[PDB]
Length: 7
Length: 398
Ligand code: NI
Ligand SMILES: [Zn+2]
Image (cartoon, rainbow over all chains, first blue to last red; front, side):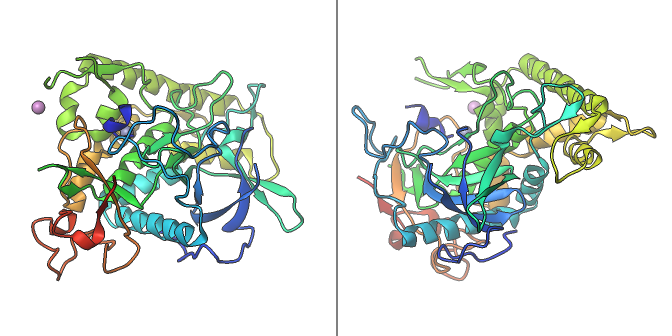
C-alpha cells in the first residue's frame, strides 16, 4: 500500500 | 516466468484457465494460472470482502490523486484481456532482474502452513488458503495457491495485500502465512516530482505489493499497531514499520532497532513452533499429498534442518539469512536499483497526480526498459517516465 492511501 | 501468453478469451480447461470461487467462506469468475501457486483474476475485487460490491464513489469520497473511482473500469472483455497482459508483462519485468527472480521464487516456495487441524498430531490445510476450481460436471475441486492478483475494489488506485483471516490464528504474523490477494491495476500509475511530472514505473508498484506478500506468506508481517510517528517535516501522521521495511533504503532510519530485535526473536520462535508441529504430526487429512511430502514442503519453505530421524529444527544462521532476505533485501528501494528507473527516494511523500496508461503495446513499455525504451527518444534522462515528454503514454486524471 502506498502512503498516499492513508489519506 | 509466465507459462503461456494468455488471451482473456482463451477457452477454459479447468487446469490453468478456469472459472473459480474464492473463500467467503459469489458466481464463479474466470481466472488464469500464470505460474505454479499464482493466479490472476481480471475482475474488480467485489469478492475478498463481500460488502464492497458497490463500485460507485461513496458519499464523502476523496479525490485524485488520493483516490479514483469509475464503476465501469475493468468491466469489458477487452479491458480484462489488457489487464491480464499488463500484469503478465510486469511479472516478466520483475522476473528479469536477479532480485525479482529471487522474490518470486520465495513467493512460490511460501506455501501457507497447514494449520487447519484442531488435533495437534494431524496436519490439515486451511480452506481459506485455497480456491475452488469448477470442473466440467459443475462440481468443484479445491486447489491451494499462494498469490492472487485481482483488480481493485471501488477505489481504483487503492492497491494493497489482503488475505482471509483465521478465527483465532494471526496467519500473517505467526509464521504460518496465508494466501495473498493483491488488489492492483497495471492501467494506472502515479506522478511524483524530481506537479508530479514523472510517472512511477508500475513494475516498482507491483514489486512493492509482492514484498508485502512475501512478508505475509511467511507469516512475518509487522503488526500494523507498530508505527513511527512521522517527523521528517511540517502533525499527526503515522506510518507502520511494515511499510518502512517494505520501502527500505533511506527509510530504515526510522525503524526502532530495539523493536526490530524483538520482531526477529518473535518470528524465530514462531518458526520453532512450526518445526515442533511438523515433528508431532502423526496423520494428514487429504487425498493428494503425503505427510512426508508436506513436511518436505515446509522444510524447504522455512529452510529447516532435518536430522537422521526426520526431526526438524530451525538453523539460526539459515533463519537469519531468510529473514534478512524477506525483510532487508526485498525492498522497493532495492528494486529501483535493479530497474534503473526514477522513483521516490522515501516512502514518506504523497503522490501529486494520477495517470491512465497502457503498457501492453511493445512500443509503449517493455520487459527490459519499462517506459524508457532503448533506441528511442525516450531512452535517456528517464524521458519515458516524463509525462510531458512522453505525452502519448500518460493521460492525467481529473
Ligand atoms: Ni533523511
Ligand atoms: Zn505498502
